[PDB]
Image (tube, rainbow, N blue to C red):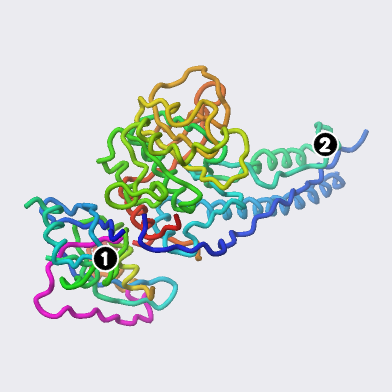
Amino acid sequence: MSRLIFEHQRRLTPPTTRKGTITIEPPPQLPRVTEEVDAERADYLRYLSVVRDNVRAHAAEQRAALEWSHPEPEVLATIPGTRRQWERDPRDRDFLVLRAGRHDVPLDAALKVKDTADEIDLEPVAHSALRGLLDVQRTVRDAPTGLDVAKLARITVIGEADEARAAIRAWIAQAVTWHDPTMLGVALAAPDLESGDWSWLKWLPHVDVPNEADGVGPARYLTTSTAELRERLAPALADRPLFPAESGAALKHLLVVLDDPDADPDDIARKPGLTGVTVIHRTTELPNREQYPDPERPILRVADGRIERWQVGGWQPCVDVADAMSAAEAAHIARRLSRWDSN
Amino acid sequence: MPIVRVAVLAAGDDGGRLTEMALPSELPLREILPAVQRIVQPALSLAPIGGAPFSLDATLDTVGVVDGDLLALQAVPSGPPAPRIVEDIADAAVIFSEARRRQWGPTHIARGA
Amino acid sequence: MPIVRVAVLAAGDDGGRLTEMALPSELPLREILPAVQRIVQPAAPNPVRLS
């Protein structure tokens, strides 16, 4: 839904991250059976300090890359109408990943130590410093992490209505303001679409069904029940293989969101699912030892700004500061996006 | 399609409300203004937020508008609409540094005490 | 309706511009900031939301 044309030029290259695996020489072995060992550990600890600095530079580089790709939601209002408006294209490593908050994501350049001996027959101070370094430095701190749409088929979002809709709005905004309308579509089958928590999609030029016009403007995917939604959605995913298998066709890994907690998501997709469908449906029926760590159908609940997954038992924290946005910010973004289309 | 889906803000008597509405883009405003008047406020022209109001003898397309723009319902100026003039500022640090200055405020009295 | 005539200046990293504005003041800033951006700018640094 736009009365103006957008043209896709070269994506602005992100800050260059690299995967140079840093190798660390093991601690010196203790005297095989004192200034000697003092100088030894002094040399090792200086080497360790500089390699600490180096790996911290690697981590800050990774984090700057991830923050270039996943900005804070409040920034998204400035993206549209810019050289970077829909930059991610299916060659990028950040395609179809939507930020869900800041969490400690492990390093992208795994540290290593040459495997010769890893016992405590080594220097106490040197080996202690190395173990501490390797224990903390695994992760970068508070980097924007996200959900990979391509490897998801049902994202059952347990939780309070307000916070659940906040997180879902954050994801849908983060997606639709980084992807073309020909590479990502959005559809919503909610009980009521007269309300600001989902009305904002009215402008979004990614809920429009291609080459149909119902009422004013091009016809939109917003509906009032899963049955009517699937009716309006069939000839845009009823040519697609099953979800796990691969396809060679160009296709939109579109989003479908079912605000209705009652609605069973089996009335849009099938049980194995479709390729390029992401059923982001909220419910309230909590699970209990329904063990499914499968990262293709995750059950994640938002509590007070912290999204928790259901891996194998108990709620395991997946993020720490779960991003969220209002209906107002989403309305503003949706307006600023309705000025461009290529569909 | 000759449609533009704009978000007109209402005549505030309870607060401004972004009533979204679709407007025929190729039609002169003399016919759609009474309609949108009926819509936004249950019962004179449109203007971009900071800009100058559009002429009643024009079309939304010609003055230029797109499906995401915000139009406020105002009344055309009695006299001629006048341009805004930009004052070139060559240093903002001094305005900020002197706006952070108060002559003998209660803070000075606290310091002296 | 209510309106208000306020003067704004962009500071930025370059010699900004002070201009008047006739802004309607009944609605959240998020709906009027892009208007100010269009006015006082002559229109990536890792862009930042401006208010």
Q: Where residue A151 sits: x, y (%)?
A: 57, 37
Q: Where residue A123 sits: x, y (%)?
A: 81, 38
- Name the residue type under label 1: His
Label 2 SS: loop
| Of the pair A219 and A164, the residue shown nearer to us | A219
Task: Name the image quarter holding residue B51.
Answer: bottom left
Quadrant into which the N terminus of chain C falls? bottom left
Q: Relative to B67, is A68 on the left or the right?
A: right
Instruction: State the mark number for residue A60.
Output: none
Q: Which residues are magenta?
A: B69-95
Q: Relative to C32, is A91 on the left or the right?
A: right
Q: Is residue A300 above or below residue A330?
A: above
Whether residue B97 appears in this view of the structure is no
- Name the residue type under label 2: Leu
Marks 1/2 in contact by CB < 8 Å: the verdict is no
Which residue does the numbered mark 1 point to in the structure image? Answer: B108
Q: Where residue A206 sits: x, y (%)?
A: 41, 49
Residue depicted at x 55% and y 23%:
A292
Q: Is residue A219 above or below residue B107?
A: above
Q: Where residue C36 sits: x, y (%)?
A: 31, 67
- Chain letter of mark 2 equals A
Q: Residues within 10 Å of mark 1 (few under 14, many from 20)?
A: few
Q: Relative to A332, is A314 on the left or the right?
A: right
Residue depicted at x 83% and y 47%:
A40
Q: Nearer the viewer, mark 1 or mark 2?
A: 2
Q: Is residue A215 above or below residue B70?
A: above
Q: Residues within 10 Å of mark 2 (few under 14, many from 20)?
A: some
Q: Examine the structure image and report whether residue B86 is included in the region drawn in magenta.
A: yes
Which residue does the numbered mark 2 point to in the structure image? Answer: A122
